[PDB]
Each structure stands twice: as structure tokens, then as C-alpha cells.
Length: 306
Length: 306
Ligand SMILES: CC(=O)Nc1ccc(N(C(=O)Cn2nnc3ccccc32)[C@@H](C(=O)NC(C)(C)C)c2ccsc2)cc1
Ligand SMILES: CC(=O)Nc1ccc(N(C(=O)Cn2nnc3ccccc32)[C@@H](C(=O)NC(C)(C)C)c2ccsc2)cc1
Image (cartoon, rainbow over all chains, first blue to last red; front, side, top):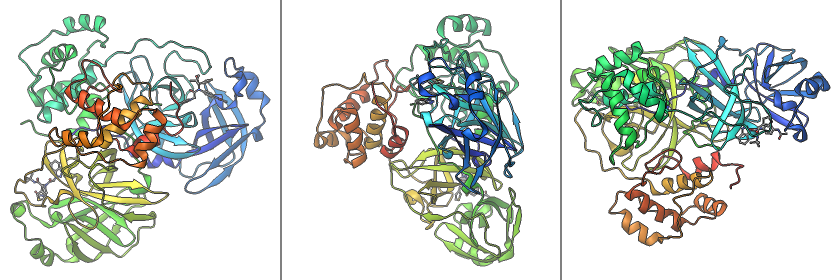
């Protein structure tokens, strides 16, 4: 029992982190097969940050403009033999395949989804933590500028699914990045301009999962006979910065295991949103919306209702 | 910017996890050089879990009683050639040295310290998270049945410092384990027999570090001209379930870079202990006490205010 922010083990990803340097800019890259991925803003000099011409920058660089090095494990200096843009990513082809390339896929995650982040600095892994893609397609992580190129991923059946490369910090504690097809998460540009975020929202289904986790962990004071219809909840959600609720099988199974209905949990959200009455749930006095139903399922596996 | 629960990257530790089976019981072990460590209660049948005679169990076991396998990476079946007891740990000697043994040390952390945990199941690493040793020397983690033998650790300069092997759950979300000298944290016993936990307390020095981290991240509404001297806060602490405050250099450094005095933070604590009055700090409406001053230093390295 217990519920904590848990990440996927980072070893397979650590084997792929490298340092990329272009001019006086340096950040992290991801080395898979004969390719190194890193944010394209590595090419942009500080004085062009507000209006970069990335097409111009790209072909103003030679291959030997890029220095790519692996600092950890089997160290190496890697020769770049081609460079091109993939959306807001720079794709460096190098002349040696990473012998430690894991089995991997690329995916783009949806708002509400969690993934693990390996934070890196200067081509060295420094920390691991888990984030959730926010309603406005940002994340709440912990990064420095040198952390650009840090990698988000999930893991299943020994396959690493790479889903995020860190690109920038928008506002205090608020970050975004791109998937590895080079599409930036959200409506964000890799420029130095004031950009406005769409308003964030609590992810309802994640809050519901969290409330089920709580009940399975013996915390159930917030459960009342009170229920609210899904249609009524969703109306209310529109005006109170919560996502619409749509049921899933895993939520139904958490309901079955606890004996607490989905409608009771949505009612509890409406009451709790108004205030926690000086009480806590799994140690918090605010709604937690970064646990998916799948994240919860992993940490309550085999846990029996009491 | 941003402050999250960060763990040390797990790759170096993943390479040392194995599965240990003794009769009907299976759990995780840690393989370093020619040694495999695992909890000694692997020797105990479901029956005599109530009052095990570990000394008798030990002599009834032969080296062939113990099956040790590596299921990940370079797989391996390891032959046990000696076994001895080390407090609440079993120390198995195997005929093959782990080729991927990292540079390592052992240590025993003190209440208030943080460390990373690699949750394991059937000898397979499944997740990483960070915990904090509570005032009563328990940790608030997330552990399921076959997670015994899961490993806690910190990183010290290319050196893995092993500090914890998971032993048992005491109550919902409440766990303990041993250092690798085989001394149980909290002196709890590896018996069934329900044991009384000392009362937990908020770690004052960590709360203070968290408030500094808040101030360093633009959240500063709680700071008042109000001060309260250390001597006075400590008297108050004894009656309100906080640990007594003792100044350290890292705290001084943070007070220094914030311009906010320790006495001001202690004041905020007494006030915030009364209530957050509807407001939040770093998104929470409760006092966070699981970030050490060093943890915070790390995530505020190279950060200047507003
Ligand atoms: C030569 C040089 O200085 N290059 C550079 C500068 C800034 C960034 N940005 C980051 O977010 C860098 N970054 N990424 N993670 C960070 C965490 C803390 C601080 C900064 C962080 C973007 C941005 O908007 N930054 C401000 C300062 C306005 C917030 C950006 C992207 C393309 S152009 C500008 C990227 C590259
Ligand atoms: C064959 C067999 O039954 N083996 C076995 C089972 C359980 C444990 N325990 C764990 O905490 C195992 N453990 N460790 N973390 C857990 C999280 C959830 C559930 C179980 C967990 C202890 C305990 O509390 N057990 C009761 C029965 C009270 C539940 C314990 C420690 C020394 S003696 C007994 C140890 C060995």
C-alpha cells in the first residue's frame, strides 16, 4: 500500500544521453541508432533568440559545427555526418550507432497522460521524476536551461516509449517540449516572445482515480451517499476549470473493488473543490490530478478493500 | 525552476537486482561482487511468521535451498556457496561476481534524510521514487507483497550509497527496512506481532527548506516581518508535533540567497500550522516536510529571484 509519484526505471535511457555543443550553446541529446536528437534552438545565438530564422541557421552550420560527446559509461566522441530539422528538433546523423540502443518506439501523449522524465545536465543524467501532460499541454517539472534535451518516456514489456524532449520554460514552474516527430506540445513556439497559455484544468478522471487510491488505502471520510449525474457534473466542470468526465473500464474496476460509485466520486470532487474542511486525503489538502487510473492500478495491485 | 520529488537515476542499481527464492517464498535481492543480500524472512514459512526462530531456520537451510536468478540484462543462474545472517538480512555468497557492480558504499541515514528507492518485484525493477526517513524512522512509500528486498540508495560522486533494503509494511502507506549492516530502521522487528509506532513529527528543518524553495520560486505571501527566535520555536515545537530546529550551513545559505531570515520562516510555520487560510504554497495547502535543505539546494542551483 501507499501512493507515491513513481517513475519508470531510467537505466535504458541513461545509456542514450549525450552532450551536444554548437557554438557557445550546449545541451543534452538523445542517441538512438546512428541518430542524435536535440532541440533545434541549440543553433540560435542569443542575439537572434527573439526572431530566429532556423532554416538560415541550419545551413549556416557545417557538420563539424556540432560536437557530440558521451560522458558516462562507454565514453565517446561522435562525428556528425549530416544535420537536418525535424519540426523543432535537430536531427544529427552520426557515424556510429549507439550499441546500447534499447528496443524503442516514439509516441505522442494526450493531455491527462503521465510519463517519466530523466533530467539531464551537460549530457549527464541527474534525476528522475514523473509528470503529467496538463490540460493546456504544458508540464509541471523541474528544469534549468542546461536541462533542455531532457527526455520523457514510458516503458512497457521492455520497450522504451520516448514521448517528450524538453524545449523551454514558459513561466515559473511551467515547461513544454516536443514529441520526437518534432511537434511541440501545445500552442508554443521555440522563440523568445510572450506566449499565453490556455487556462489549465484539473483532470477529472485522474482525480477520481486518486480518490479510489485513497479509499483503497483506508482513507474514506470524503465518501458520502451523495451522487451527481455525469451530465450534471460535466456542466459544472465547464464553469469550474475541470475536464469533462468520460468513464473507462479501469475506473469501473476501481469502483467494483471499493464499492464506491463513479457518481459518488464526482460528488466528492464538487464538495472537496469548495474546501477540504480542515482534513487531508493521502496527506494532501488539495485535489491531486496527476495520477492516471493506470498509475493507480499499479500501486494498488492486489490491495484488498478494508 | 519548479520543485518536484526527484530521484537518483536508477541504472547502476538496476544492474544489481536479482530474484531470490527459498522454498515457497520469493523476493528481491541485491547482487554486489560475490554477495547477494536479501531479507532474512525469506527463510520463514507462512505458518511461523508469528514468532520465527531465525537461528534454527538458518541451520535447517542448505546453500541449495536458495535459488538466485538474474532476469534482466545479462541473465544468470547463480550458485549459492555460503549463507550467513547479518541482523535482519541474509548474506548469500555466490560463485560469480556481478560484472556490473558499481563503485559503492553502505550507510545508515538519520531521521529527516531523503533517499531514492528502486521498487522491485520478482527480481525485476519496476519503479523509482524518493522517500524521507520519518521522525519515528519509518518511511511513507509504496510497496506491495513481493517488493521485499527493494533497494534504497543515494548517489555520491559515481558511487552508489546503499542505505535501505525493504523489509515490511507496518500499516497503510507505512513501511520499514534495514540498512545493510542489517539493523532495522526504527528497531521494529521482522515478526508478525503488531508493533507500536512512536508518534511521527513534521521535520522542521525540511519545512523551512521548502519555504525557501517556495520563495525562490516566486511564492512569498506567507513571509511576514514577524520573527520567532529558535529557542522559543523549539519550546512551541515540543507541543505541536514538530521536531526542534537546529541551524545548518545549507539553511544559512538559503536564508542568505532569499534575504528571508530563519526566524521569519519559523514564524510562518506557527501561523501556517494554524491554517493556510485558503491560499497555497507551491500548489499545496499543507506543510511539506520531505525535502531536505540539500534536495532544495540541488533544484535551485543557478536560480535568481524576482
Ligand atoms: C543562447 C540562448 O540563450 N538560448 C536559449 C535561451 C532561452 C531558451 N528558452 C528556455 O526556456 C530555456 N530553458 N529551458 N528550461 C529552462 C529552465 C529555466 C530557465 C530557462 C530554461 C526559451 C525562453 O523563452 N526563455 C526565457 C528566458 C524567455 C524564459 C526560448 C526557446 C527558443 S528561444 C527562447 C532557449 C534557448
Ligand atoms: C510466506 C509468507 O507469508 N511470507 C511473508 C509475508 C509477509 C511479510 N511481511 C511484510 O510486510 C511483506 N510486505 N512488505 N511490504 C508489504 C506491503 C504490503 C503487503 C505486504 C508487505 C510482514 C507482515 O506484516 N506480515 C503479515 C502476515 C502480518 C501481513 C512480516 C515481516 C517479518 S515477519 C512478517 C513477511 C513474510
